[PDB]
Amino acid sequence: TGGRNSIRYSELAPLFDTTRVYLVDNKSTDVASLNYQNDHSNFLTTVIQNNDYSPGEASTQTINLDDRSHWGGDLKTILHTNMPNVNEFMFTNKFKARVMVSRSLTKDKQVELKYEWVEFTLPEGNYSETMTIDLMNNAIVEHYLKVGRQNGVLESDIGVKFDTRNFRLGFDPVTGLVMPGVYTNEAFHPDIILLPGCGVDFTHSRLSNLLGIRKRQPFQEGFRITYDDLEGGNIPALLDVDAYQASLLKPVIKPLTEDSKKRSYNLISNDSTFTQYRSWYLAYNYGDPQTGIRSWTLLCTPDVTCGSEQVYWSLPDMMQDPVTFRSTSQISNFPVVGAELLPVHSKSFYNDQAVYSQLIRQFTSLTHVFNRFPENQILARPPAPTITTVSENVPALTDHGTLPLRNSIGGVQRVTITDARRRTCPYVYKALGIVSPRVLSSR
Amino acid sequence: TGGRNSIRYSELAPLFDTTRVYLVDNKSTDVASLNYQNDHSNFLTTVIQNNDYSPGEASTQTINLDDRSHWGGDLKTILHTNMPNVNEFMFTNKFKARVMVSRSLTKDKQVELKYEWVEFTLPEGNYSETMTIDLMNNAIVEHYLKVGRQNGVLESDIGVKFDTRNFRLGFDPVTGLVMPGVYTNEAFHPDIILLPGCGVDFTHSRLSNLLGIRKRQPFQEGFRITYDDLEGGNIPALLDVDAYQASLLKPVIKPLTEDSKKRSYNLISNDSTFTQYRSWYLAYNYGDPQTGIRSWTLLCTPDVTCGSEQVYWSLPDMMQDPVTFRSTSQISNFPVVGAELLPVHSKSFYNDQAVYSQLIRQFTSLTHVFNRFPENQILARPPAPTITTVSENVPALTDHGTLPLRNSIGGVQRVTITDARRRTCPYVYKALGIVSPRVLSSR
Amino acid sequence: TGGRNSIRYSELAPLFDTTRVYLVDNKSTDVASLNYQNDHSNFLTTVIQNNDYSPGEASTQTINLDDRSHWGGDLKTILHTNMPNVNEFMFTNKFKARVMVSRSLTKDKQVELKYEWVEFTLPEGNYSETMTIDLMNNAIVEHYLKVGRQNGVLESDIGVKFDTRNFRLGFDPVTGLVMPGVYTNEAFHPDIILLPGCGVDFTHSRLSNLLGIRKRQPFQEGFRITYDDLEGGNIPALLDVDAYQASLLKPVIKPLTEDSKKRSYNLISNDSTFTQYRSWYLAYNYGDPQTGIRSWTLLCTPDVTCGSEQVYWSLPDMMQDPVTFRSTSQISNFPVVGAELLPVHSKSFYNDQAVYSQLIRQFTSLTHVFNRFPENQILARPPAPTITTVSENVPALTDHGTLPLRNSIGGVQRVTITDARRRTCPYVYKALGIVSPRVLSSR
Amino acid sequence: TGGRNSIRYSELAPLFDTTRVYLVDNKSTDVASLNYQNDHSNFLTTVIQNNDYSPGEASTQTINLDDRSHWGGDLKTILHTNMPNVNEFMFTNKFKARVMVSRSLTKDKQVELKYEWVEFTLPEGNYSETMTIDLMNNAIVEHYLKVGRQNGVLESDIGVKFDTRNFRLGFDPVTGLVMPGVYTNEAFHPDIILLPGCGVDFTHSRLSNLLGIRKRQPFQEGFRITYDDLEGGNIPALLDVDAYQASLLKPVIKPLTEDSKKRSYNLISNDSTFTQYRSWYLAYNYGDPQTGIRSWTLLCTPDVTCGSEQVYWSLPDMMQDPVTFRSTSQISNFPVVGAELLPVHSKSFYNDQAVYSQLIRQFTSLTHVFNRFPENQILARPPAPTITTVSENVPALTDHGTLPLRNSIGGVQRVTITDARRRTCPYVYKALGIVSPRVLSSR
């Protein structure tokens, strides 16, 4: 320690024992000269914070930690993002699903309905755990409006629909039917996937996390759930309110075959006490726990963030690249000095006006856009949850610890916030660096 | 320190004094090759973060900390879960209770009513301190609808019911009765257990914690509370509003024998100023503090989490297994390097619309599903609390400290987040590891 | 350091330099064998985490830190409680006060009214800063209903009442009276104590903290406040609304002698512009700041916790008992290794529906139980505050630092969370311990 | 280190290397004997935590750190206060301002109105950022009711009034007037000061911070703002709604000279499109940025705390009094060992029922006490902000670091939490101390 601990600049002053180097994006001089066509998750800083020098010719000068003992440096970072929820880079703007396109051209008198897989798109910015559902449901429907009805497909033949409510709620075991003729419009958190003949696919989406459905073995590439897979679910049929309560020697056993503005419920047969609409939530809970989707998958809470993936710092013109890491110039394989978690968490709130979520649309815009089928008790406006989560960005200010330090530091350091696939994150508005060099050995 | 502190990789570079090794689940290469049928609470990582190598043949290479001094490593971990409240692994989906099945087949003119213990089931996902009550109460009732009424059992003979309100509130000491003829519908936190002739059992449930009832000596395996145990409680009888207020030399002494839609209150006798419905809350508070259930148990606040049990890290192809720990290959007895708390806490909110919790059901769905008996002032819809708690998952980012380190580290480390019974937790979506090796001795 | 740093187990392995010992309550084996009749704030743990041993015969084995250098151990603890607000152990369930019992038997034509001190009781569980007031007020009244009215005492003779509002608000200095004939029903935080002829006493209560009234010199045992002490307060009289507004040469000077359902305001005389009802808040603020209760006491914010008292860890079969501490076997004098704060804080919220706190009772239950006197503007339902605080339990996870360590550690450590009077806290559901032994000297 | 590190008590035991000393207020024995007439921000503790000793004769005994090496001690403290917002010690209960007393006795027919400075007083407890305004405004008015009207002063001659809203909002540049005849009743945060002929003075108040108005050079003793200083503000005149909208060639140019219940707006002349009422907010924003109050002062956010001043620990019978500090016995100059921030922060909330803040008073009490002039659009009830802040007390638990330690420690330490003027803070209900002595040198 007491030997050579010198930290010499240019023709300035020896300051022996530990000092500060600063990795700053905001440097008024350099912003123009370098970083012109660079962001905040990939940039160059002048670490010669000397006023009297050309930020070009600053590169010439060396920091020079003493080359008699091995230096280390304590690294602190201040990172901040403005990343939303649903996004391009995050694969949270897109999801795939199967819908019907053709409704039975009736070739030689017989019903031949076709199906197809399509990639729905979302409009980035938005971020509610509730309304992110409604948005997908809108773009299942904005598809029907573009192709479905135009080639014959009925409104009662919708297909993929993300609801949130417990369907087998209200069900009576002897009736085979839901007793108060309306599915209990109270949200039950992991939003179901409802399907007849078709299905979804989050095989390249993180939105499956927003829904709170996850593969029980999730390193297995390929997450697709279909109508064949949802077996055991099968949302029970309603019950004609009026064909018992306004009648009545008992006519109990009457399912609500159609609805208000004449929308068929596609009941299996006239005998059946079930509809052909199938529910993930009921299959995960009320289906066979060993044969079907409870073995396949897992009931998790909705993650409004969709991954909470880590970012990694690379400081590779300063720090001694750690063990095993290639010393490279590929911006995609830069040695990692430290790894933060990407600074976004879920902040949950309460709101009982989820009951008057209905009294949202009525004075909102009277549009019913997230509500094309208010009369139908399936394809309906999904209820809202009691607790809404919003992906909130927050300042992360974390100590990466003490890293080994090279003893000749260019006045032009490169700072890089890579992601979990070592690509730049373009939502990093503010990255920062404080390094504190200090002794460790001899030679 | 200044002697041999070498950290040598393969045919790469000696980096002497402290560096970083990374335990990452997200590694793009290995996710396919290994971990295919593994989760995040049990996995293998390539700790050779070298690009140019076969993730199979990476296993060959050694990290090699110098074998001249004993190394240690500072361990930091970033753990995140998506675990809900009520759950399968957590034993929060099931509870046992006693209900009546048979109502008096009347063998040779005499009332012979039978009882049985049964295991009610919950639908995992959901998580409110209020609605988690309502859900159990629903599945006490969904049972009656399956067996009870069908073999004779009356609606006035319900049995196990979890309400939340102070019953002896409103009570007048000379009347022997509740004066304004309605039990004061304001929630008083630990939700009672109400019973005649029957009882509950949380002997294999953590839901007893949700209720905020706990054994005063809780290591004693076996938590069951019954009607015999609740002695002293005995919710006082109401008071016929109209047989005093519309009456009139005073007819005060009239209990409300039945209710609105003719539901008997099972009063002990016509003499008695009490009902046969018994309350835990009244027994814990107003019963004999030494004879009954105040000595047996404890009034705690509701824990929406139901345990806050710890998890444990095991890093056993890296860390020197601590004192006493067997060096094993049983995935269930892997040496523990560190112990976090399982990352879920209670976030409480306020809502005065618990008063208009009634005005929840009326515009919710008009279903009254959590309210089959709105007229009856016992078996009624329980009130909601003023402060509702929700089990919120949160990122845990904690320093486990500096652990001893083996000096030859395979490029294939195994990371394992075991639980309080050393079994894998399948709610761990993101586990992470940063290790910082540093010197400690010589030989 | 480099000499003898050996940490030897049984016939296992020397792991030289620092390792982990774990103090766990959850250990599956020992929960049965030991701790059977023990809680979480007093227990025994097997610190031999070896699978292959009898948890009885584990006691035999020694941890054995090297007896050549003095060891220390870094101690981390994870503590969690389920303690409510109002409680038995916390002395927050009970308070004393003086009420009248006898209203003038009129021995030889003359009004002789008697008084007595009594101990009111609360029903543990509950915890609001507002409703905790209402509950005491209820049990001032539940007393009147048991003895007061029965031996003659009028409703207009209530006595001890905890309101929250500024009384001298609305007062006009020339009228001697409150101008809009209603005391301004907006809460002003430290809830007053209102009294004629009687008083309160929190001499063995922490509830005086909930009220936000504190002795200015609070180590002086004995906190009782009486009508004689509250001098200068004297809530001003109202004003007969109708005997000015429906009148009119001005009749201004008419106090509201009685109220709606004929309840006297006990005005000093017909001359007096004051009532005999006295207010702590007015005395603390508007009385003589040197002669009365502003010198006696202090206006603090309500503490919904009632003390935030510290707990203490005692690890006495492991840690070297610190300086001065007796080496004992009295579970009440066990040496302290560390002291946390008992893990409960106040979480405050906002609610403007404190205005419609009136519209709470009307759709709550229409009971008016915390409101027996809605017409009377003194004994009335107190208003609610704008900011309500609730005693929330939270996980405490704190570093107690590095303590001296005995070098022969029994496989049967005793962990004890004592309180500020060294007695066990029976609200501790989860206690935990992580110890990291490391070197300090030689001999 | 390895030499003499002995820590010897009495006739007890040598515990060599680091241990714990505890500074506790709660000690059952001493609370009676000493501290009887002392608080928690100034007390004596027995640091001999030995049971078997007279707390008097404990003073005799010495802790005795070894006098061969210089000791230090790591100091941790747990501090908690119950300090409100508006207060006596904090100078947040008082403020000075100028009002008129005399309205023109008209000596020889001519209007001679007098003015005077007075010290308004607040009732300590209360603490809202909104209602703390309303309270001052009340005590501007409670003054008028005591002296103003009685010596002639009109209600339209009020003077000092603290509103919150943007006045020049609604203003049309060609009309010279506010177009919808009502000043836009939406709060705009730093509450103005409104004045004609008079002014305020926070020269000994921290309430100027609550208002969010601050001297741009604030070390300059003396903060007084007057009508002469507010030049350029001059809230524009309204507009007679009916003398344009109900009249059909345009009568636009009619100011609302009086109001509803005949209250003059004191317009400069009949010509003028401004009123004589002047606004700080408009002067700070719309006046000359160089000539007037924008140069004088600064627009800051409201601090509900009013200062966030620091407290200081003094441990002067233990710690070696730091550099420069006099070794004294004046309780007002005790050496400082550490400095915390006084544990109170602002917790902000949202409430849109600030719009129905009007529908607060109507069902509150119908008192209009903070609203004597509801018809008048200046002297009116100020609007509420969307975000209300409340001064919340919180437990502070902070590491003051490692301080030098005297090697002979009396069993009677004195703990003192001084303020920013080295006087005791009598809001400190719980102070605590953990010290960990450890070696530093030799002699």
Image (cartoon, coloured by chain):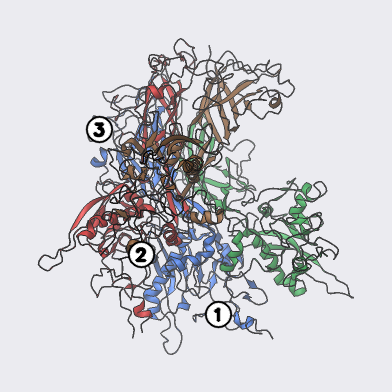
Chain colours: A brown, B red, C blue, D green
Q: Position of residue D284 (x, y in %)?
A: 76, 50
Q: Give me the C-alpha separation between circle 2 and circle 1.
A: 47 Å
Foreground mark, 3 or 2? Answer: 2
- Residue hosting label 3: C58
Check chain identity for marks 3 and 2: say if they share one.
no
- Of the numbered discs in the image, which one, if any, rests on residue D177? none
- Residue hosting label 1: C267
Of A390 and A402, nearer the camera is A390
Q: Position of residue C31 (x, y in %)?
A: 27, 41
Q: Chain ID for label 3? A: C
Q: Position of residue C79 (x, y in %)?
A: 40, 43
Q: Residues within 10 Å of mark 2 (few under 14, many from 20)?
A: some
Q: Are marks 3 and 1 in contact (CB under 8 Å)?
A: no
B75 sits to left or right of D399: left
The kind of secondary structure element at disc 1 is: loop
- Of the numbered discs in the image, which one, if any, rests on residue B374? 2
> Image quarter for residue B273?
bottom left
Q: Residues within 10 Å of mark 1 (few under 14, many from 20)?
A: some
D10 sits to left or right of D304: left
Q: Residue furthest top?
A: B11
Of C141 and A129, nearer the camera is A129
Q: Amino acid at mark 3?
A: Ala
C46 sits to left or right of D313: left
In the displayed structure, would residue D282 be above or below residue A78?
below
